[PDB]
Image 1: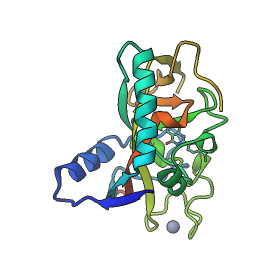
Image 2: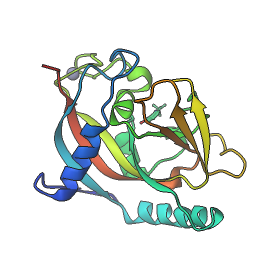
Image 3: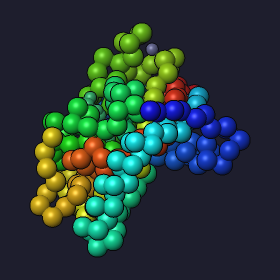
Length: 209
Ligand SMILES: CC(C)(C)c1ccc(-c2nc3ccccc3c(=O)[nH]2)cc1
Ligand SMILES: [Zn+2]
């Protein structure tokens, strides 16, 4: 049921998504081990992901959450990187896309920092890097990320020193780095229907000059 619609680079929509990508790159405490060494991306393509069934699944859950949270969906646009990006855009998020060993519990994780999600494109810890070169810092191979609509509802705030159920009375967890003041938040949901993979971004990381 999914169709992908290319956005033109001359479109404000493309430009806004690229700006959110580029402006949320940060340095990581692993010195680039997982995601590579880079300060910016080369954006190759941005596609809108259209699936009526997955969209209706998402809005039905958003409505349930919104009503449970006194008419506040607390909806965000957040990044998600995963080796299962192809499966997600076709079948939606589900328990197979959860990070069982994540710090904030076994759920599906999303990032405000695009570079945080970039660390998971090739798997946990960057896996073995790109298929072709086995390089986690590969500047040649094409990567893909999702920029997703995520319903947080009542979110449990967990400060961090950097499929399960939600904390009782909560629909998500907000993981907020308390040591690195330039690190943005990470968010966890425990139901696949609380996210919709709205944009598919194809890119390369760029070698710093
Ligand atoms: C275990 C699998 C391979 C299914 C998996 C594990 C973790 C992520 C994942 N971690 C994240 C952790 C924090 C913030 C964003 C992300 C993110 O963007 N992605 C994706 C897939
Ligand atoms: Zn490569």
